[PDB]
Length: 307
Image (cartoon, rainbow, N blue to C red):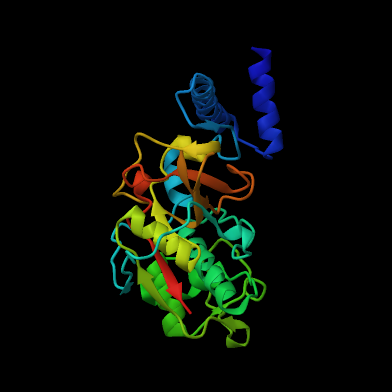
């Protein structure tokens, strides 16, 4: 009715959308299907069938093809070439951890029209380690990785891996700050300048494919880089609460993110920092189901750098 037409017009304006005559038609269809599922889902939430709610956002008119192109960023083959993390049995991890309260985490960033989640997950873990080492929080450059880690196996906006990113930092002897090497969301020439370098003696460690191990690692090291299966509109439109997708895969992770802590609702979850801006989820964060048989592959390809 008039309400639907009005809401569509408002969303378009709000997100500054200008479509051609033919596109307008199918973009709206995409948007309406999403609005319908968000509605049905939220009703089921009220009925207690879900732990999280959904809400329309800037990705309301996006196609699955476009999603795979700019929202993700992880490569198919995920090799384990880093040092090994041995789960300490005689260490008892706390019930909850949140590194943002310790000042290990920088503000939420936005990868934009570039499938570079690998770069954001990488700098995220590095920023925490540098803070653990200097007590100084400096935002690192994702653009540096995008433009320079090609030899390490990365493909800029076409995907890469966090380990390849950590490898680059090793071989290179440093990574610039975001202030000196701004994010452009595209592949340009490598402008790495030593004058603004940080993390000169790096390396990386891979964590076993177990949540118990991942938990002990987060509690003792700081934020950790993890890969998750994010290809679901439930995640795309996630709003708040504990995210749980029955159709989530524990083996096909396409999105790189950062775990900054874990806890339980006073029911356990992982505090995850995403790079889709503050307008997504909980200020750019998502509480993901913990200890639910490696939900979304959270513990299948986790690692952290060493400085």
